[PDB]
Structures are given as C-alpha cells and as structure tokens.
Length: 56
Length: 57
Image 1 (cartoon, each protein chain N blue to C red):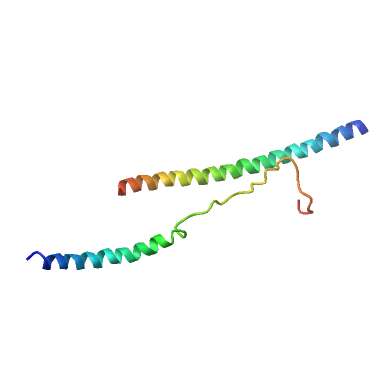
Image 2: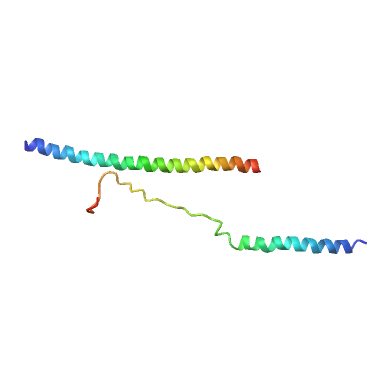
C-alpha cells in the first residue's frame, strides 16, 4: 500500500522537475545573452581647441 | 593700430577659443544634461520599475 503511490509520485515529480531541468539547463549553460555591455563614451573632452578639417 | 589690431586678433582669437571652449563646454553641458536626464530617467524608471517590482514582489 506504500510502494505504488510512491512510484507514481516519483514519476510525476520526474516529469515536472525534468521539464524544469531541461529548461534550466539552457538557462545555465548560456547566461551570456542575458548579460549587458559597458557602452563606453569618448565625449570629446577637448573644449579648448578645434579640428584641422575644412568642415571644422 | 597694429598693436590694437594685434591685441584684437589675440583678444578675438582668445575669444574664439574661449567661445569655442564655452561652445564645447556647453556642448558638454548639454551632452551631460542629456546623459543626466537619460540616466535620471533610467533611474526614475529603475525606481518606477523597482516600485513596480516591489509591488509585484
């Protein structure tokens, strides 16, 4: 009386935690696309002089 | 005349350079204000989204 419902619970937890597991696999093996970037700036710090080109 | 003309080309060049400095400094007052507002807006939004995240929490 104690073994059958145990086995059924094992199967159900297996299927659910296993879909959870296969998707969490994709989450963990690649966590790079969920990252970000520094996005630096040059900002042209030279407001003391101008440029050589004809347009400037 | 040459001294005033030269003192002028120099006051005027220093002026074009000071005006340029101001133009560029102002270009940056503005670029900084744009970044400040973009970041303050992202911050206010982070805080709106935080308040939301906290409400959703």
